[PDB]
Length: 387
Ligand SMILES: *C(=O)[C@H](CO)[C@H](O)CCCC[C@@H](C)C/C(C)=C/C(C)=C/C(=O)O
Image (cartoon, rainbow, N blue to C red; front, side, top):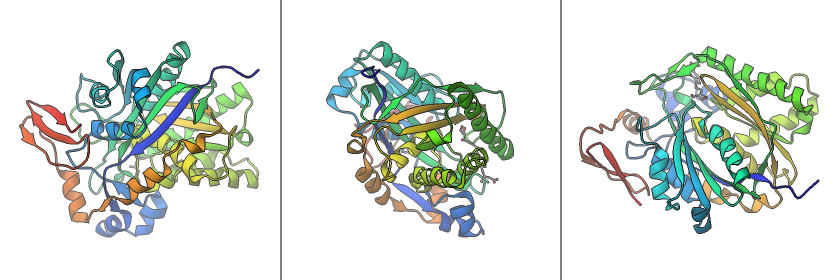
């Protein structure tokens, strides 16, 4: 049968701060071969932000790129998935709801589970719309991935947000009901209260990440009978581009030469933008989706897209979407390329200073920044934004 209600991603966009540092410049400052960052790790430009830009700034900018008048009237749920919260009680989603001018009778909250938070939001939104097909949900991934100067994870760093509008009859990606979820209690990466930077066991994280994909994939294959041949492309959450390729490589070892090339070529398309941005944590998978859709030229209506989401801790999920005819007319390629091209290239000195600076919310202060939705002042610990 056809004619059934479809539910999924109607519009999607990302935002990153107007600054970056080139990995060659970093490599040289770190006394390391630039090839080690550019190729070994697989990153080219690291998105960096000043203290006048937080998850609200990025979420607001990303969402503003896709929301229209009618969307703002139909949205009754606003969700932010993040692991970079600025408050322990008040959800960042509440401020986003105001800044976006969304209609008042909506619920807003924050979801936390490492880089999986936005995925939890996406699937829950899907179910919400299934029961309420006239309504829409704003789901935004927002994060600031900082490991530390001279840390192993430094070259993988990034910052920004990915906003998605979930609705019935979505114009881009129709989501399936083939979800396979997994939870394991593992301390590969975490951030205890009071830690500005994360605790991380790189080895354990990479091992758990790779095995988590294998595990949900095998279960999915067992439930559905679908194999890699049945997927036109796969989008992955990734800690960094090379590790993503390694998780994929590990699982397609038994595929024919031609299918490996096809699948790997798709992966390369999915990491175009990540190479110029770095890790968005919760937004990494969905940046990969945008990148795939905007850089691929042979993808078409009806194609099946597999999505692997991961959260340290650890949680994982594999689910499927189908490209909706006409989707190529509802992307934001021009805007994204302009967004990436109009950034300032920071010197190592400028980078390390911006990175080190900290916002002390206990001190009332004023902050100057041209970016819309940036922090304009702190008063009694309360952040004011431009609007
Ligand atoms: C998301 O779930 C999670 C953040 O919570 C993220 O995907 C992974 C975080 C940890 C990833 C590390 C493996 C990054 C890193 C330290 C790698 C390198 C290059 C360092 C090294 O010492 O080799």
